[PDB]
Amino acid sequence: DHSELLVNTKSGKVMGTRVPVLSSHISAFLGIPFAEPPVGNMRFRRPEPKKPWSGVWNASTYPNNCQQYVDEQFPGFSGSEMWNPNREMSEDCLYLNIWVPSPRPKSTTVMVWIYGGGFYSGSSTLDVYNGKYLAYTEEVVLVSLSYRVGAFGFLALHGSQEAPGNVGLLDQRMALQWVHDNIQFFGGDPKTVTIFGESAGGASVGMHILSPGSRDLFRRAILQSGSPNCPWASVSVAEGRRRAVELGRNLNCNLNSDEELIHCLREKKPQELIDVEWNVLPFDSIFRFSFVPVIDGEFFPTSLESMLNSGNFKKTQILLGVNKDEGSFFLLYGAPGFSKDSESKISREDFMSGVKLSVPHANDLGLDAVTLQYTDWMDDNNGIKNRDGLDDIVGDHNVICPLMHFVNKYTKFGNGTYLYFFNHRASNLVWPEWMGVIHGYEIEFVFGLPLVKELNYTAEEEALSRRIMHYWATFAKTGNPNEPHSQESKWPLFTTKEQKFIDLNTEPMKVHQRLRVQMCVFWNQFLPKLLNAT
Ligand SMILES: c1ccc2oc(CNCCCCCCCNc3c4c(nc5ccccc35)CCCC4)cc2c1
Ligand SMILES: *[C@@H]1O[C@H](CO)[C@@H](O[C@@H]2O[C@H](CO)[C@@H](O)[C@H](O)[C@H]2NC(C)=O)[C@H](O)[C@H]1NC(C)=O
Ligand SMILES: *[C@@H]1O[C@H](CO)[C@@H](O)[C@H](O)[C@H]1NC(C)=O
Ligand SMILES: *[C@H]1O[C@H](CO)[C@@H](O)[C@H](O)[C@H]1NC(C)=O
Image (cartoon, protein in one colour):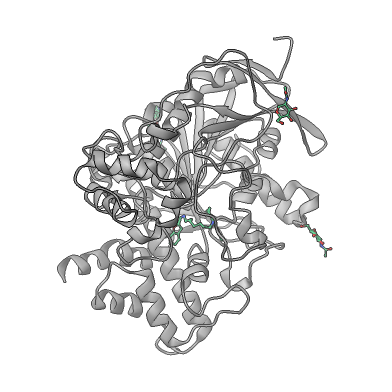
């Protein structure tokens, strides 16, 4: 080798870069391709594996982020801008990143990060997805993948093979193929790969657990605030088709045959599709899960629920959880009365509307049912209560109760579940109090940022991040987040009978049972039953 930053891989030779890590240093390989650029006539198709290359691929800088809608609701605002692309956007975007410990290890554990963003945005290159503190602190090879989002990734004319749909999931699978085939040269154990991810990354993980074509490519799985059965995470092939033809209609396109339609859509510039993306949604939910995975009979042989009942999925160990206020950012962005700079107390009227916004698929009875469920009628004009109740509505319906359904289903067949509730609101949070513990805001703990002194996290936050990185890495290494026979308090296994989970915050650990049963019984059993009858 005569070098640490040089690696020969079944695709090509790769030149690394040396990086500082809290006064130490590590190796890092940025922007390694794993597939052919999906440009021109390749748009909306299955990816192809990268054609192997003569020479030294300069893997010393982050790659172009994929093409997505950017978030300008708060220009200049870091809380919101941290999530936007920070490298140039381009259809040429299927690369990946490895952080290897230094000195290069023998065959140690690999974690692969799959970003979220609702399947319409996201980027592998964000400050908070910086793999170096975790790769360093826990001695793991940390990969981060990238995948087409939006129409580029999920336009779906089932029957067609030109835009079959799901292709963004296939992007991830191929990144995962590549880890299977090449991570050995980098010091990592291809028999010890944990895929982890948040939001749509969390659901993508769960979809790889489910899909036959992906199960064999990894060992263990972490799902953070996302689950494949989330209502924003998939659509029927009928509704993908319907939505895809509506992108044509919106862009003046021939609609007689798929060939016609795809051809038209392939001619248009990127920002053009992005600009009419919103306008495919029936009406509506706020924000733009236009193009998402399809239940296609291929990647997904049958319906998720049926897969999940029959046990048709990978049986291994999972670690997963939710944040206390998943819903808060949705309300801020899409619902009246809710604004970044006020306490956002909610009139009783703005509650009726907010309910309607959050449960689009429901009839008047559904809305009454949800309203009854979440309303204190001894004090129905409390604007804090109404504001918080709406938050819980949105959080439970879209993240917690689908996640709890998945957990109870998986655990009947799987080989060990661990379940967390992250309810710490960070000291240095730039968002207003009423949002609480926000969708996405445990990521920074997982990826080590509170160990950087520059960023003003408290010491008790430094200890939390260290504890969490350990749980995560110990779990990836062993299928269990606890240390062999250590003094520290044990995070119990989640079981069907007893359903224990822990909080994840600065106070000493507490174990609980049945995370949000009452509401989840409502969302998972009662409400669907009531809508199917009426
Ligand atoms: C209620 C209803 C639907 C929901 O779907 C999801 C899962 N993914 C949604 C992410 C797509 C919206 C992201 C646009 C802004 N990017 C952010 C993202 C996240 N958190 C944010 C918090 C505050 C402001 C912006 C955030 C975390 C996920 C990455 C994108 C969560 C969720 C909650
Ligand atoms: C995970 O699976 C392992 C192995 O597939 C299970 O361990 C076996 O348990 C049976 C009965 O408990 C024993 O007869 C064997 O000695 C164990 N085998 C091994 C290889 O350890 C284990 O119980 C499963 N874990 C969970 C939490 O479901
Ligand atoms: C790798 O690429 C970047 C792009 O500007 C450059 O800064 C860096 O010095 C290059 N290294 C080599 C080996 O050329
Ligand atoms: C704490 O650090 C931040 C960096 O995000 C810095 O901008 C800020 O000025 C510091 N706080 C105070 C009170 O000076």
